[PDB]
Image (cartoon, rainbow, N blue to C red):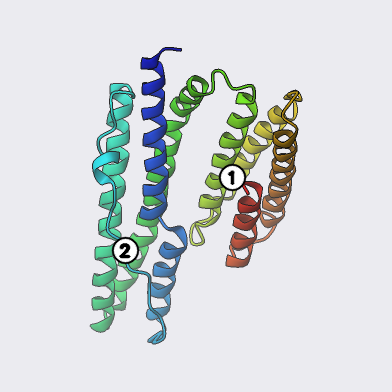
Amino acid sequence: VSTADIENAAEVIKYYNTSLGVLKDMVKEKDVNAVLDYMEQKGKTPALSAIVPPAVVSKDSAIVLNPGNCFNEETRRNLKQNYTGLFQARTEFYANFDTYLSYLKKKDVTNAKKLLDVNYQLSTQMSEYKQNIFDILSPFTEQAELVLLVDNPLKAQIMSVRKMSSTMQSILNLYARKHRMDGPRIDLKVAELTKQLDAAKKLPVVNGHEGEMKSYQAFLSQVETFIKQVKKVREKGEYSDADYDMLTSAFETSII
């Protein structure tokens, strides 16, 4: 591991961290759910008390649209394509909301319903582009970690926490798709999480890191609790915010 390797690896992780924040901001799943819920309700009643969450201005678009040469050209292309597609779908989704309200003002329920249906599809697309970006990055961030943790006696444990935390967040982001739940996809990701947890459970005790070992095994126990909760929620027939918040809370406690 040279200084060039280290810089490269840092740049990869930098881009991931910026991406995590940007995608959190650009697809706020509960806000998107809220927009769609208001659209549905406004077609039934005036829904006079509602204030739908406004679309925040894009931050760090200069960074995410310009992935560096720490990624290969194909990767750079695919990242740019997915971000570009995301920003376009999001623009449309929010433009369409305004137009929808104007069709309703004109009593044009027929055209309003069609624009609602288009927005359900744009919501799914936004979420797909977001997950696509994480999926693209995953192999490269794993390589970057190996460089940065090369001399760290807890590299395997550290990497397992980072990997499983990403998988839990991916499951949360799917679960939040209230209007178009992909049950089998959630099950697939729970099976990935389970494989990660099985791998983690094989790791040895590292001598002289008594606190870190305790911390790590508490995390593993919480991951197992999370897996079991997601399975129980998957036996139910509809999304609920209570279930989402239970799961997100289970996640947050694991990373404390």
In the depicted structure, whether residue 205 falls above or below residue 247: above
Under circle 2, the secondary element is loop
Q: Quadrant of residue 128?
A: top left
- Residue 46 horizontal/vertical position (percent): 37, 87
Please tell me which residue is depicted at 68% across the width and 36% down the height of the picture: 194
Q: Residue 250: image x %, image y %? A: 66, 54
Residue 62 pos. (x, y %): 23, 42
Q: Is residue 123 left or right of residue 73?
A: right
Outermost residue, top side? 2
- Helix, strand, or loop for circle 1? helix
Tell me, yes or no, whether the two marked residues, 2 and 1, touch with CB atoms within 8 Å. Answer: no
**Badge 2 local density, few (<14 within 10 Å), some, or many (20+)?**
some
Which residue appears at 32% of the width and 21% of the height?
A: 72
Tell me which label, 2 or 1, sits earlier in the chain.
Answer: 2
The residue to which callout 1 is attached is 168
Q: Which mark is residue 55?
A: 2
Which residue is pictured at 58% across the width and 41% down the height? 165
- Estimate the x, y position of residue 163 in percent, counting from the top left: 57, 34
Foreground residue, 164 or 12?
12
Mark 1 neighbour density, 10 Å: few (under 14) some (14–19) many (20 or more): many
Between the residue at mark 2 and the residue at mark 1, the CA separation in whole angstroms equals: 26 Å
Q: Is residue 32 above or below residue 157?
A: below
- Drawn side of residue 245 relative to residue 1, left or right: right
How many labels were placed on the picture?
2
Q: Nearer the viewer, residue 243 or 210?
A: 210
Identified by mark 1, the residue type is Met
User: In screen coordinates, is 213 left or right of 21?
Assistant: right
Which amino acid type is marked by label 2? Ala
